[PDB]
Image (tube, rainbow, N blue to C red; front, side, top):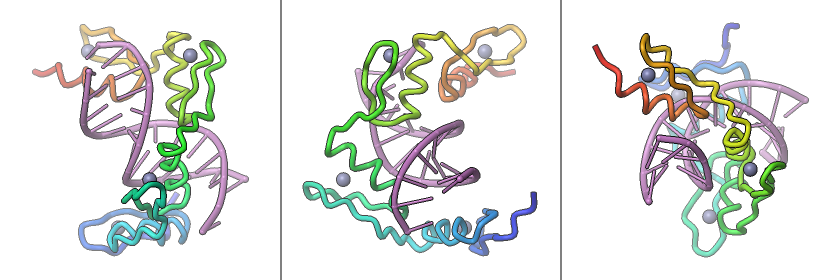
Length: 119
DNA sequence: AGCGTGGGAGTGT
DNA sequence: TACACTCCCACGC
Ligand SMILES: [Zn+2]
Ligand SMILES: [Zn+2]
Ligand SMILES: [Zn+2]
Ligand SMILES: [Zn+2]
């Protein structure tokens, strides 16, 4: 499980299994973002081409992922997935606090809830 | 709230 | 590198 490709940038402990992953990560320290958005004077740019393509759905308005329950359409597949939990009632994130037995559909819901517990 | 919805990131083919 | 899937974090209401 050892990651041979380690970043040598000061203060960074990132390591990867592939050289391409490390080479892509190195663009974070250099700021290189070769994939610029050319829609309607947009200033967004990305180090990865797939991040640009996902972003450009903002301009085209395309919602490729449709809920098979309520037929609502969504720009991203991960947001479709968490949306469908509003139908199924799946809540895979439990608090684990002694008295609290609340569950949540998304991890960021549980993170906000955990902030209420102390002592 | 609970949940829409974006960037950033890791990893799969 | 292209493309696809997944998860975290964040903002907003
Ligand atoms: Zn680094
Ligand atoms: Zn754009
Ligand atoms: Zn739905
Ligand atoms: Zn709790």
